[PDB]
RNA sequence: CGUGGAGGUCAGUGACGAAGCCUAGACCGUAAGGUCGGGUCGAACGGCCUCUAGUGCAGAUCUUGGUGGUAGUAGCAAAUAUUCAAAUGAGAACUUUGAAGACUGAAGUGGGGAAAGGUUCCACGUCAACAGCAGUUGGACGUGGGUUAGUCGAUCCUAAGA
RNA sequence: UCUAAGGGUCGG
RNA sequence: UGUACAACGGGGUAUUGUAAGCAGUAGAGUAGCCUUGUUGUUACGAUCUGCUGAGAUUAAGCCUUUGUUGUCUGAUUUGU
């Protein structure tokens, strides 16, 4: 997932099972003050939902990755 | 099955998270009897029956 | 085996790096003033601007010497500014909480320069002052008193003792013992277990060391050793007004050095590339601020597998003070008028000296007591 | 003693393979050649060159040449001294026909 | 004669050793049995007068468990077939790499799917058990990683029927 | 190793 | 340490039926090219003839051997 941040302008999140691509994009758009290109999602085999959120080219996910504070 | 229902996959996920050895520190608990995960399961030894 | 084991040219490279270290240190001390005072002059001084200024000055000044020559020169130890009870290694990232100097703060500035791998390290302690134009003569016609004075005088007298004792023929243990005696004279304690290293070309951390105030275990694990002509040491005195048992307190480590003795094939491309970029650096220690996000992830795997050694930010108890003086000295045999005897040549210079009349303590080194006779003689 | 030689030998594989189950012929030729190396120069540790394996198996399981001209050199063992200090290394000799020849000391320089 | 429990009594025996168990050692009794020594053991137990029964085993193709002879025996023979070397390893017929020899022969021992399984997929570590020889190998053990859709499905439609 | 027979296209 | 033994090689005995290579005014013919044939040559051609009862195999439970080469004291028991 980290590689996706470094190389694909993608933030990766475990996200509510009950969410949806709209509801996820909105939350990402507001918790992080960033704009969003599209969200893909899948249901991981442990029963959680993971969301690939690609940011628009105005943003660098790696920047905003380590603003949030992981790496 | 591949195209599998959500109910089934859910049950499948739970059934997978239960599939681990006993956490070793339980053995250190006081008055502990549990030596090992006696309810443990394997795809090639016992089917789930859905 | 190096031919020549020592040369005039090597002494020159140490002296020139020392001149730079001394100049940069003094510049940073002059630039240290309260935040309010800095404001009156259209500037701001925090735990960040001074570190950035120091490092940039080291690079600029080293850039001006040995011009057009195939070599390496620059930072041997990144500018670190450790205030009050903070012991060492504070050099914040742009994203970390900065620290803004206050009037009366006790400040330790620690930095190192190298020229062709020959290292000149220095550190100095002082107390912050308002702008001279706003309070002309006030800070000067006053003295520092109390525990701040106690710990600063103790640390400087420990430095003076070490200058006299770190010479060919003496043992490292003699220094350790003297430091405890001097520090206790002021009801202070040298920080347990901290090391002063022999320096060699490209080597900031020689295995031959002087240890401060060792625990019983540290006494067993640490090697007794005799100083010899042609050796170089970065003597580092860190003394506390408290118990002297420095601890980590959750502060982010920013200073690291590559350890060429350790090898590991890293799993992540970011880590491998970070490793490669680090090995391009001259000095053993560097700050992560020299990279910020992509360094943070590369650091993780490298530090985990011991490829990078951290220089953690340690603290004494809140309200206590830690003072530091560090100087680099060149020990060697002087054959004069037929007699050969070891003499030490300090290269830190002006940067490492403090104005003794600024500090007034209730205490002094006592030579009458069975317990401090001889120390007074040594210091005079 | 133990004296490091190297001779050249023709083995009659035909009379040694006579009767053998077809799927076992090339395999026996391997065993039978070791047995030969052992017999000549009592070595016990017999290593076969892969070019000789190839030679042996060149017409597949069933079609072993009737004679092989072999090169067998007794040699010194190296490392964690396996039971015996000595070798035999066996390799093939590129010759026109294996018919006609007698065993020969190869002088070793 | 002997057993579980009950009322009464010996102010019964006992951690300085109760009960239990072992003993071609001893003694009493026609016998059912009783008693003693020695060894082992560790917390309770017995005699006498009574009371009471879920009260005494060799068998029931008895019940449950445990164990033998059989016996290191029958066997581990379908599906053409293996060989040389190096590497690794405490250890190599069986792992990996190389070479050779062969086979499946596209009606496949190739490449995908449906039902079904459910993580067996991939990586790192790794052999106690399991793979009816072996094992450093694995569909095994431990720890992790992994499934991205307006356009492929479900979803909509109607079928027998419900 | 030979023999013969069995088509196409385009110009009159 | 031999009138030894073995591995090879040699000779004999057998089996099969004439090896490879070369050569041929041997070969039904066809087709090219030329100086157009007292033997014209070039390509192709199953096969045929010679060297050639040749070549291959021959103890693995054949026989022999003036050659070549090598081998020749490891283990365990036993007494009236």
Image: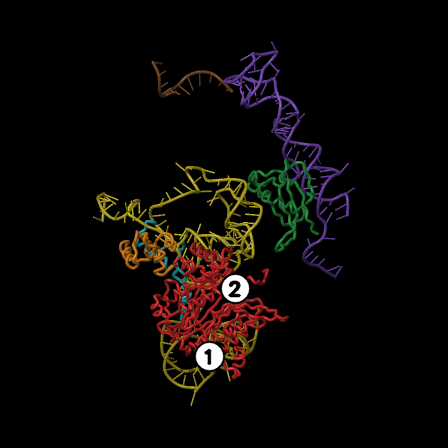
Chain colours: A orange, B cyan, C red, D green, E yellow, F brown, G purple
Q: Is residue A11 above or below residue D98?
A: below
User: In this rendering, which labeled residue sits more in front, label 1 or label 2?
Assistant: 2
Frontmost residue, C8 versus C279: C8
- Say which residue appears at 48% left-offset and 69% top-offset: C350
Separation of marks 1 and 2 at Cα, in angstroms = 34 Å
Frontmost residue, C87 versus C79: C79
The residue pinned by badge 1 equals: C186
- Say which residue appears at 40% left-offset and 57% top-offset: C294
Drawn side of residue D34 relative to residue C269, left or right: right
Label 1 in the same subunit as label 2? yes
Q: Hey, which quadrant is residue A45 in on the image? A: bottom left
Of callouts 1 and 2, which one flags the residue occurring earlier in the amino acid sequence? Answer: 2
Drawn side of residue D91 relative to residue A39, left or right: right
Q: Is residue D20 visible?
A: no
Q: Hey, which quadrant is residue C34 in on the image? A: bottom left
The residue pinned by badge 2 equals: C14
- Under circle 1, the secondary element is loop
Q: Is residue D103 visible?
A: yes
Percent across and percent down for residue C126 are 43, 72
Percent across and percent down for residue C226 are 57, 70
- Under circle 2, the secondary element is helix
The chain identifier of the residue carrying mark 1 reads C
């Amino acid at each position: 997932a980290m590689k996706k941040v470094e190389d694909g302008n993608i933030l990766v999140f475990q996200v509510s099972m009950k969410a949806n691509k709209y509801q996820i994009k909105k939350a990402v758009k507001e918790l992080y003050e960033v704009d969003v290109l599209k969200v893909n999602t899948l249901v991981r085999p442990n029963g959680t939902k993971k969301a690939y959120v690609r940011l628009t080219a105005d943003y660098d996910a790696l920047d905003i990755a380590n603003r949030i504070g992981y790496i | 099955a591949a195209q599998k229902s959500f109910r089934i996959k859910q049950k499948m996920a739970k059934a997978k998270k239960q599939n681990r050895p006993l956490p070793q520190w339980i053995r250190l608990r006081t008055n502990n009897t549990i030596r090992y995960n006696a309810k443990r399961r394997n795809w090639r030894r016992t089917k789930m029956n859905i | 085996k190096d031919k020549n084991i020592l040369q005039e040219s090597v002494l020159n490279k140490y002296r020139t790096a020392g001149q730079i270290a001394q100049t940069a240190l003094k510049y940073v001390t002059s630039l240290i003033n309260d935040s309010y005072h800095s404001k009156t002059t259209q500037r701001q001084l925090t735990v960040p601007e001074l570190c950035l200024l120091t490092d940039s000055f080291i690079l600029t000044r080293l850039e001006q010497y040995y011009k057009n020559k195939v070599n390496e020169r620059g930072i041997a130890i990144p500018t670190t500014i450790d205030i009050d009870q903070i012991s060492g290694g504070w050099c914040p990232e742009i994203d970390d909480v900065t620290g803004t100097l206050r009037p009366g703060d006790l400040v330790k500035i620690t930095l190192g320069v190298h020229i062709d791998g020959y290292t000149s390290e220095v550190s100095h302690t002082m107390v912050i002052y308002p702008v001279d134009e706003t309070k002309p003569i006030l800070q000067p016609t006053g003295p520092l008193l109390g525990g701040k004075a106690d710990a600063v005088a103790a640390a400087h007298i420990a430095m003076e003792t070490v200058v006299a004792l770190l010479s060919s023929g003496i043992t490292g243990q003699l220094i350790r013992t003297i430091v405890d005696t001097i520090a206790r004279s002021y009801n202070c304690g040298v920080v347990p277990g901290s090391r002063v290293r022999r320096i060699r070309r490209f080597l900031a951390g020689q295995n031959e060391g002087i240890v401060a105030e060792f625990t019983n275990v540290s006494a067993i694990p640490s090697d007794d050793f005799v100083v010899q002509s042609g050796e170089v040491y970065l003597i580092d005195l860190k003394m506390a007004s408290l118990e002297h048992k420095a601890g980590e307190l959750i502060a982010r480590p920013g200073a690291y050095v590559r350890d060429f003795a350790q090898t590991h094939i890293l799993k992540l491309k970011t880590s491998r590339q970070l490793l490669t970029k680090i090995d391009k650096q001259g000095v053993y220690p560097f700050k992560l601020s020299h990279l910020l996000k992509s360094f943070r992830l590369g650091m993780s795997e490298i530090s985990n597998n011991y490829l990078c050694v951290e220089s953690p930010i340690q603290i004494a108890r809140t309200s206590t003070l830690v003072a530091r003086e560090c100087n680099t000295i060149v020990l060697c045999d002087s054959s004069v008028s037929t007699t050969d005897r070891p003499e030490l040549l300090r290269l830190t210079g002006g940067s490492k000296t403090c104005q003794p009349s600024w500090i007034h303590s209730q205490h002094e080194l006592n030579p009458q007591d069975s317990i401090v006779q001889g120390i007074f003689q040594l210091a005079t | 003693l133990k004296d490091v030689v190297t001779r050249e030998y023709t083995i009659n594989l035909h009379k040694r393979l006579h009767g053998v189950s077809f799927k076992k012929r090339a395999p026996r030729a391997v065993k039978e050649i070791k047995k030969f190396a052992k017999l000549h120069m009592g070595t016990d540790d017999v290593r076969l060159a892969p070019e000789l394996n190839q030679a042996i198996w060149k017409r597949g399981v069933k079609g072993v040449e009737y004679r092989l001209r072999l090169r067998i050199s007794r040699k010194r063992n190296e490392e964690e001294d396996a039971k015996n200090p000595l070798f035999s290394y066996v390799e093939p000799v590129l010759v026109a026909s294996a018919k006609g020849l007698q065993t020969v000391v190869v002088e070793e320089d």
